[PDB]
Structures are given as structure tokens and as C-alpha cells.
Amino acid sequence: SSFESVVVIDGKGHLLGRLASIVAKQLLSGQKIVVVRCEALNISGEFFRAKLKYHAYLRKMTRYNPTRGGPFHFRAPSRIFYKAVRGMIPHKTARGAAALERLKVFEGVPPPYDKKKKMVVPQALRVLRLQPGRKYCTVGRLSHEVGWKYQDVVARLEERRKAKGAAYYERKKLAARQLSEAKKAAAAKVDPKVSEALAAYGY
Amino acid sequence: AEINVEATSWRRVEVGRVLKLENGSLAAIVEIIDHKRVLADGPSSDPKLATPRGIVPLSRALLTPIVIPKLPRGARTGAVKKAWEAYGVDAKWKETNWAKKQLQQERRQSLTDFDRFKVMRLKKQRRFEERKALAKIKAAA
Amino acid sequence: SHRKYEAPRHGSLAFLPRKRAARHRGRVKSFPKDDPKKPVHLTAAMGYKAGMTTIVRDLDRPGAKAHKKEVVEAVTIIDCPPMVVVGLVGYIETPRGLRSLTTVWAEHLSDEVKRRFYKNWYKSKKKAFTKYAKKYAENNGASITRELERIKKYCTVVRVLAHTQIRKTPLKQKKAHLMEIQINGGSVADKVEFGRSLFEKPVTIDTIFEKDEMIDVIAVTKGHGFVGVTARWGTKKLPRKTHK
Amino acid sequence: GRLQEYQVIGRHLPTEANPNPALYRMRIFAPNEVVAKSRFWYFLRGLKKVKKATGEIVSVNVISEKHPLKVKNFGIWLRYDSRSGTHNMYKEYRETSRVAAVEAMYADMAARHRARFRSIHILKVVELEKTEDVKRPYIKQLVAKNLSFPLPHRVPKISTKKIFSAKRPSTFS
Amino acid sequence: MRYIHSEETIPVPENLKVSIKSRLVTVEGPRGKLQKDLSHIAVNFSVVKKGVIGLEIHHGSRKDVAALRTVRTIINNMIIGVTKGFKYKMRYVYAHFPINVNVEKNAETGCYEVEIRNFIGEKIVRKVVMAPGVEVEISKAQKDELILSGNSLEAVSQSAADIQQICKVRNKDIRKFLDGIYVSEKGNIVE
Amino acid sequence: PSEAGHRLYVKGRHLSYQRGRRNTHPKTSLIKIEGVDDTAAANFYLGKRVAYVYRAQKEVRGTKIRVIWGKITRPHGNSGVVRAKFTHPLPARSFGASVRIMLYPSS
RNA sequence: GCCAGAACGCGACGAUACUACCCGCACGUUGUAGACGUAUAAGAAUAGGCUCCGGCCUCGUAUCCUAGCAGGCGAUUCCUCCGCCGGCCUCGAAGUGGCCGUCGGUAAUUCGCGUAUUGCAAUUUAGACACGCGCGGGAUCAAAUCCUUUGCAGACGACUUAG
RNA sequence: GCAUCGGUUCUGGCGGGGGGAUAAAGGCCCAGGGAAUGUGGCUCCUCCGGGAGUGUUAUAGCCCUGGGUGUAAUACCCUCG
């Protein structure tokens, strides 16, 4: 338990409801959250059942005027995740409104938030919660078929980003190699007793 | 007929294995009661590694790479103790990677406030030497 | 209780908002799909409607009742004086749609276009692109030639700004019209160089279209002030003896 | 619950036409020595004409396991009530104490047949003496020669209040 | 009731090679290469002896143990297919209207495409496109025989089914109108 | 020279009041302590004092900063939350704000 | 494909007088759902992986930074670490980082002077964002509405035009 | 604000006593009897890991009955500080 300034959650491999509940507690506490890669969340069950649940959602609409009041059905993966979170917050009060202002959700990895450290919530990871043998789906596929347009744009944009992040990895490996080899050559030069003193204290 | 398979390999639950409980205790398996529970005993002179006789659920143990060779199942505390000392289980486990890392854990927690000051200053002195060496190799490239 | 005799619906719900158009000039909402193996070419034009008249021709339709006989058909005449390219714009792709990021105008502009950026042109100083021209003839158009490279590097579609010569028509208006035309060229380098060549030089419609081919027409319909239900949707009238 | 095995001894009140009545002994599993006596009277009212208002309780003792660190196989004969009749059952278990077998049996019956504690009678419990008299296959597999088996895909344990881990866990422990 | 150990084995002839990695099987022999992705099944592969493949499942249920024998025959088919190929035959059956077939090899797309004309005296022309790796031929030993062959059994059989399913009769008795293209024998290329 | 920090307290957050499901009691407040999980750890901070500091608009005696004082009374639940009583109930708009927890009454 | 375009969704461009715009610090009314080390960039699998190929290693209880009147003045002693500027490359998803140079600061070792009195506790007033002001330097000299007119428009406003 | 008290109350640690089969088990020793998911030997098939049969402690061991140092220790319940 700690209080950071802003924490960045990587959405790939998490469960929709089991992540919204964790995140919705943090917002009301006073934390700031940023969810990235919502195109790659997960839902338990089988894909066809997710369709049926969503089609039953698309049927609700105000009768006398479909341009006011009626449930507006957003189609993007971030907006699906955002709807889940808004369910778990008293969003009709000033306290709830303020809490929602502390959240940001995107597709892909926008410019400000790449080159940062992405956390992981192990109380909602799929490979840890679900039982081997059952089936699951992906919000990305679900949203594409209910009428989301920008799958291929975000697909190829992500490909470019991960290509840039390969030369960077080689620099890190080079930097580590130099630090490790320097330690082996410098430890023996001049260190009569400091070494044993540190080793006894546990370092 | 060359075959190259790259798969996983776990450690088995058998008679002779030594489990590591949560409170730094060791025990040796004597008979497998069920899928989730086994019967085990660890006789040891060191009062940190010794454990009573009883049932232990497998969801609260860790499989260590030590295994007593040819331990008859259902043995008694006396016979298991003889095999324990003859193989030297406690001696073998001392140098294992898990032990060393565990040993460091208590030492760090024991640093007194004055000791924290000294280690911090001592670290700086070693750091200074390391910083010089890195610059030399980095500039040379 | 249910409706006694069934009947279809009066009017269509597809064209639902029956309000005055937001702008007087028609709006092309989609251009034909791009194909990178053709040669560079424009994909639209614009003109003025003159009137209608009648023609006579012979039909060639094997199997019809009027095959190889004379028919009478109505036609319409559109008056199309040439257009003048003024600049080009480039769009890139984003996870929220397309967006433009650069424009590069030509060195000299006409009074016709300059009159479009003003609402009271008579009592004005007419300083529309005065300082922009100084970008030309300064460090040899360095600022101009960098934006073009940017379009070459980042952009994925290119469009051309063009305007009409309304002084060559019998109209009383003097303010020209301006719009955009997309190029379906074959490569981004090709379709930006072709656009550059056409700066401040007229292009005729016979280079755009060709005879006996099929086109689409966009415009704004005729206006009626404020009408009742019987004429607007087309419902039956009530009997002669109805009060109120 | 948490059970234990009691021996309960009871008797009919002596009378002038019959002094020194007979003594009846039963073995009862119960959480404490209050429900122990109640179960005794309930089982006795169905076999012989004795109440509690006209009887008395001679003794109540606790039976403890003789070798609670040895593994052994058990067989249980029982009867229970369904929603539409009564039936007989026979099941087998593998553990180290008789009391636990009754603990395991109660949980298993309540899970697989929706049979509460109210409607179950324990006819007999006996530990299988040899190995060749085991019948059910879900235990025959557990007494095979040279048994050994890995444990794949076991989740590691993480503090329920350490949110926001910093790297991907691994299930190869 | 969950079984504690279910194991199966697969023998490999010393004419080819096989490599498994992240449940991606690759078999290569004197006739090409084949791949499959078994990531949807939780199985442990291992090498028992110098020429025997082993696969096992631990603490599986009834619905889960069923899938072991399925995997075995899938991998066996790959091994036998690469070393002996597969070959299906199909026959024409008609009463009055003869059936005409054309087989032309597509160039720059590799695969073949068949053409069926005059089916039950029909005026339409129906086209089917085979899968990559299968080769279609017209027999020369018997009359009115088609011969399909290839390396991957799944593709070969699925391509044959496409031809059979395209030729159907509608709004008639299928007990009397017995027209259509059908399969007559399945086997291997070698031996 | 001496670029280190100056902190002699532990930072906590003000979560809510003490409430049923539909009634609140502004007398006592609940606070989240940094670093404590079990209720055994929370036993350390009973009796200490806590401060809530905030900015105002006007200035009274050479300052624009006000303070409200309180102390920790007992633990709460199994997760390490504690109860606290202040000389004035907290402003009920400070849900999610940060407070300072001293170490004054020691051992 | 087609229709409307959030009147509190967004982008590119043209001309911008009046202190409305740009640059430097100088204070200080006044604002904030709430600084006090606000320090940590690979991707991918979970019935398999990482690597400085030794073959080594797999639970952030980690790594980096952390002393000096809230951090003074000098000395022995070492070329480490930090910062404002300037020049070249590079960066378009909502444009960012790198290299080089001048300058300023700097316990890895060891010392010499000063701290008191805030009196036995009382936020440690001190961080970054906007906004209003004052100087002293640079650039620049626009439009819109009413009014008259047209009828591709029209209940009146509004709209397409002309002066 | 601190120290010494009175009333109510929540929460940690330590020293004893009693009971049951005077716990049951358990370690060491003595006496007797059994088997198998049969140790070491012996025989048989394979050099390819090993497998099959005989046979009651040997180069491993286990189960059943009685006794000893035992007024043993510990678990559970109750109780004095």
C-alpha cells in the first residue's frame, strides 16, 4: 500500500469487471489512474454470449424521441470499459463527478504515456483467476463487430511503436553489460575492509 | 529420427522429497494421503528446521531440489532421522540459493538506526570507486 | 384495438431532419476509393445550372420494343467555365479520424478569391495574403519548400483547393466559390508534384470527365416557405364537412 | 461441525416388578456431550419402549483414536432420506482417523445429494483391514505402487492488499 | 473424480524429423512441411525413448482426458501424410444429362479451380477453388473419374467436400433424382 | 550541500465518516495509514496525534494556514483502518485529502 | 452508399489598430477535489521463460538517490555528479529526445571557527499550474453590426448577393 | 501539555493448579506373533530403461499383543494470580 502521483495500468490480460472494481475504489480514495491498451481486455465465457448480451443492450431506446434521454451505446473499447466503471460510482453527485475527473482511458499507447512504467493488477489477471479449460474472448473483437471503425489504424500504429522499442532494448542491454563488467574490475582495485563490512550487514 | 521438444518439467511429489513450510521449516514426505494432503516429518537438531509429526496440505509447501534416496514409505520418526543424518539434508540445504536469499532477509531487518547510517556512508565509498571505473571503460568504448 | 385496414407509411424516415441546409454550397461527403495503380487525376468539378431542353436519338438495346428507333428524352445544360488551382492540403490518419496539418497557398491570388474572405469588401483594406507572399522571395522559399516535404513524408491523402471564374458568367455576383478536390494518383510523391505543377493555371473540364460515362450530382433543392402536413408528407384530406 | 465419538450408557428406571434392568450401549458422533445424550434417546426411542422421562443416563465417555498418525481406509454403511423416499448407501474414504471420516462423509453427502444433517443414520463404520477389499475406483487409484505426480499451474500467493504489482507473475512454482 | 495420470505414445519412423515448441508442431520429411497450433489444449509433450513421442495430462477430468487420443491421431496423420501422402477418388453419376468438367491451373495464385457445366442440364456455370497444396487430376484408367491428391489430409478432404456439396438438387425427390458428384474411395498415394 | 528531505510524520488519507448503510455520524472519522495491512501493525499508532492543514483566503495572525487537531482511538476492521476524533468534525468535503500523522507520544 | 452535426467535441489557415500581441524579471492581491524523494519505458508465453552463453538464473522484503546554520565561512583532497544557456541532428497518435561547447555549483578521506534565548510541544508559511499587476525592448496600424440593395430566400429573425 | 489517582471499557504478554484411558499418541528398551503395494540375496527376458517369479530381515522396513524409566510431555476443558 503506497500513494503514488499517477499510476499507469496496462490493460492487456485483465478481466473487465474484476479490474473496474479495483480501479473504482482507488478513484474514490484519491488516487489517479490511467488505463492503457483497452483494446486487449478480456471477458469470461464464450464470444457468442457476449454478442447476445450486447444486442439486448442495443434494443433499449427512448420511444418518443431517440435523440434525448435514451441509452447512448458507445462502441469503442475504452468506452465499454468506461461504462463499467461509471456503474460503480455515485456519478450523480459532486463527489462522484470529481472522482471521474481523475481517470483517463485510451486505445493503444498515446505519446505522453509511452516511455513510462506500466503496472499490473494481479487480483484480476486472467492466467491467475480463470480455470484452465474454460473459454474467454476479447473486447477488441467484440467492439469491431458492433461497429467500431479504427481497428486497423490502431493495429499498425502499435506495430510501429513496438519496432521503435527494440533499438531501445539493445541500449539497455549494452548499458547493463558495462555496469556489470565495471563492478568485477573495480571491486578488486581498492576495497580492503568495506566489502566484508557490507557483506556482514547484508549488502 | 531426431526430435527436439522444448517443454516444461516440474518437481514431483514422491517419498523422500523435503518441503519448505512458511515459517522456515523443513519436513520429509513419508506417505501421500491424498491429492491435496500428505504426511511428512522433519527430524533436525537445529530448532529452526525441526517440525512435529502431522498432516500438511500441499497448497502451503514448496518443492525443494533435495530428495532422500530410497526412503521406505510409512517409516517412523526413528528410521527417518537415521536417513536424515546419513544423507546430510541440513548441510545440503544450507548452500541452496533459497537459503542464502532467506538468510539475507533477517539480516537486513536487523539493522539498527546507527547501523543504517554506517552502511549508507560505506556504500558511498564503494560507489565512488565504481563510478571511476565505469567512466574509464565508457570513454574508451 | 388494431388498425382495421393496413397501409404503407407516408414519407420516409431516412431523410429525417427536415431543416434548412446549414450551408448554401453542396458538400461532398465521400470521394471514390483510392487506387495506387492508375495515373494521377482529379475526381470532381463544379459549375452552374443553365436550364433544360429536348433531344432526339436512336436507341441501341437488343431485346427491347424500341430497338433501333427514335426516342425523345429530356436533358439539362450545366455551364462550366474553367477552374484555377490555388493550393493543396494533406491529411494523416489518427485513432480519432483523419485530420489536416498543413496548407501551402500560391504566390499570387485573384480579387475573386480574396473577396471570399471578407463580408464587407468595399470598405476594407484588402490585406488577405499580403504578408504570406513575403514567405516567397525570402531565403528562396525555404519555409515553402519545407511544408511540401512534410506532406511527402507523413501524409496519406492529398486534396487540391480550386475556385471558379464567376466573372465569365452572366451572373450579378462577383464572389467566387472555393472547395477541395482529392487526387487519386498512385503515390504520395507523384500526387504532390502533380499538384504543384497546376498552381495558378487553369484546368478545363474535358481533362476531368469524358463522354458517355456515369456521374453523381450534389446540390441544394428548391425552397418553399412553410407548408402544411398535406403537402409536406402527402396525407389524405378530410371530408368536406369537417369543423375546425 | 467438529465431532467426537462418545459411548453412551442408559437404562430403564428400576421398579418393584423388575429391579436391575438391562444396559444399552451405543457409539455416537456429536460435537459435545449435550447433543450426545439427545442423539442417544432419539435412536433408542425407535428400537425399544423407553422414554427419557422414564429412564436415566449411566455414563458418557470419550473415545480417542488409537493411532492418529497412521493412514487407513474406511467403509461406512448409512441410510438417508431423499425428497421422495429412503435409501441405503455405502461409501469409502482414505484418511488417518475415524472422526474425520464422519466429517468427510457429512460434507460429501450434503454436496452430492443435498442431504442435511437432520436425515442421516450411521449404521456402521469399519476400517478396511486388508488392501484387496477396496471397491470404489476413486480410492483404488490412490493406493497404486510407486505413486508420484507433479502439480502444474499452481498460482503463487500474494498479499491481498499489495495492489499494483510491477511485473508479470509466473505459475511454474 | 479426476484421473491422476493419462498417457499416450506415438512412434516415429527414422525418415523424418519433428520439433515442438510452445505447442507448435512442425513435421518435415521427404515430401514437405506441415504445421499445427495446439495452444487450445493443455498437454505436456516429452521424449520417452530414442524414437517414441510421449504426451500426458495430469489431474484431468472426463471431458478433458477425452482429448488425448484426438491429439494422437492428428499428429499421426501428419507423420503418415508427409511420408505417404493422401489420395481421394470421386465418380460421376447421371441418368440423362452428361456432366462436363474443366480443370485449369491458375497462374500467380498457384491453387487449382474446377468448373462444372451441364449439371442435370443446367444453364449456369459453377466454379470452385481448391485449397493450396492439393492437386486435381482427371483419371485415365477408368471413365468419369476425378482424382484429388495432396499432403494435408484435412485440406484434401475439405476440398473434396466442397465439390460434393456444390452439386445439389432442389425441390425434387432425392430418392429418384440421384445426380451429383460423389466420393468413392479414400486412401494413400504410396503403396 | 545537504540536498536531502525533511519529513517526520506518516501521511494518511481521510476516507469517510463512521456510518451504517444510510446514516452517518460526523463525530468520528476513518483514516488510511501508509504501510499497515493487518490489525497487529495498526496497534502501534494508538494514542498519537494527527493534523489536517489547509489554506484559507484571509490572513489572521501572520498566516493563511489553518489546522485541526485530533488523535487516533482504536483500530477498525481487519485491513488497518483506524478511527479518529478531532476537536471539530472534518469538513466533509475533504474526502480523499491528505493528513499528517505525527509520532509525538512515543513508546 | 445516404441524412443531421455535440449550439460546453476537435484540426489547418488568413488578417489582427486600441496595451489586445511577443521577450526578461519584480513583486504580490487572487485561484486549485488537495507536492513534502510525488525517482524507476522492452515485447511475449503461463502444460514455460531470461541471459553479460558461465551455461547462469526465476516471491519489487528490489534498484537509484539519501550527512553539512532549511544546510554558514576557510583548509588538505578528487575529476565524480548536478544546472541554466548556445550550436547541430531527430521527433506528427495529442510531435519529443540525443550529441557537442562555454559557464556556475559540488565531503569519495580528514580538520579549524559560528549555532544558545524559538526558554519543556503548537503547519516545517517555503512545490507547480494558471490569472492579475510594473517596468524596458521589439514587431504591427484590422474588422464587425446598424444603414441602402437583390431574390437562388422568406411568418418576423435568419439566408444567397451588391454598395 | 506532562505526572500521580478514581469510574467504565477494549486489547497484548508472563507464572502456577485440577480433570480424562491420572489423555490418546510419540522416542529408547524387553518378550511374543504376522503378513505385503516383498528389502537384500537367487532364477528368468533386454542392453534399452527395466520387468516377471520364488521366498518373511539379511546390505531397507511395516503391522498386531503385553510390560518397563513415566505421578513423562503435549492437545482440549476448568481455575488462582
Image: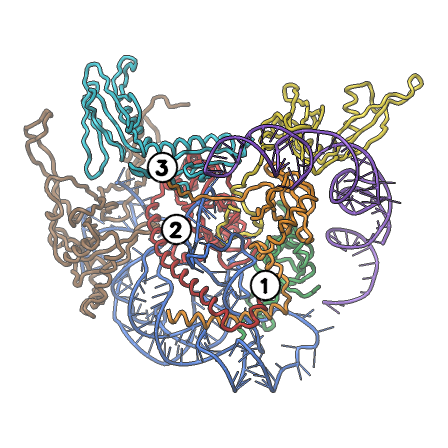
Chain colours: A red, B orange, C brown, D yellow, E cyan, F green, G blue, H purple
Q: Which of E78 and F83 is in front in this view?
A: E78
Residue underneath mark 1: A202
Identity, as a three-letter code, of the amino acid under mark 3: Glu
Q: What residue type is labelled 1?
A: Gly
Residue drawn at the location 17% of the way across and 63% of the way down: C107
In the rendered structure, the residue with mark 1 lies on which chain? A
Q: Nearer the viewer, residue A134 or A3?
A: A134
The residue that label 3 is drawn on is: E14
Residue drawn at 18 percent across, 18 percent down: E98
Residue underneath mark 2: A108
User: Residue visible at 51% across and 30% down?
Assistant: E62
* Helix, strand or loop under label 1: loop
Amino acid type of the residue tagged 2 in the rendering = Gly
Circle on res. F96: none
Query: In the rendering, at what x and y percent does residue D132 appear?
Result: 63, 26
Q: Of helix, strand and loop, which one carries label 2?
A: loop
Pointer 1 or 2: first along the chain: 2
Q: Classify residue A5 as left or right of residue E90.
A: right
Element on which disc 3 rests: loop
Q: Can residue A72 be seen in this view?
A: no
Q: Distance between the residues labelled 1 and 2?
A: 43 Å
Give the quadrant of residue E67: top left
Q: Position of residue D1 (x, y in %)?
A: 70, 35
